[PDB]
Image (cartoon, rainbow, N blue to C red):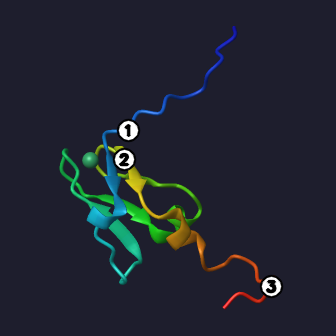
Amino acid sequence: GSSGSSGMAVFHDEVEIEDFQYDEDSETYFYPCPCGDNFAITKEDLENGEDVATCPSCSLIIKVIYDKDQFMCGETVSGPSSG
Ligand SMILES: [Zn+2]
């Protein structure tokens, strides 16, 4: 019948990107998973406002604490001629 809520936000731990390991090679961050495989989150995903790293093993999801301003600042349209 009426299911209601669809899905449940269950994270393992909120880690700051500062701890993650950015790899220019594939512009993708990494993190040590308590299961085995190291998490992975494409820089793009972050900019889009994801802040979630999935594991190719357990598929765990953690909260990536990063400066939204840092990622955001870049594509922001140009009006007053910022610079
Ligand atoms: Zn894992």
Which numbered disc, 1 or 2, marks the residue that appears first in the sequence? 1
Give the number of the disc on residue 62: 2
The quadrant of the image that shows the N terminus is: top right
Q: Is mark 3 within 8 Å of ligand 1?
A: no
- Residue 33 makes an appearance in the image: yes
The amino acid marked with disc number 2 is Ile
Q: Where's residue 2, x and y in %? A: 69, 11
Residues at discs 1 and 2 in contact (Cβ within 8 Å): yes
In the rendered structure, the answer to whether residue 36 lies left or right of residue 61 reads left
Identity of the amino acid at label 1? Answer: Phe
Name the N-terminal-most of marks 1 and 3: 1
Count of all numbered marks drawn on residues in the image: 3
Q: Which residue is rendered at x = 23% and y = 55% of the image?
A: 37
Q: Please, what secondary structure does the residue beneath circle 3 have?
A: loop
Q: Residue beneath label 3, please?
A: 80
Q: The residue tagged with tag 1: helix, strand or loop?
A: loop
Left or right: 13, with 7 as reference point: left
Taking depth in this image into account, of 79 and 15 the one nearest to the observer is: 79
Residue at horizontal 45 percent and vertical 67 percent from the top: 42
Under circle 2, the secondary element is strand
Q: Which residue is mark 1?
A: 11
User: Which amino acid, mark 3?
Assistant: Pro
**Does residue 31 sit above or below 59 in this rendering?**
below
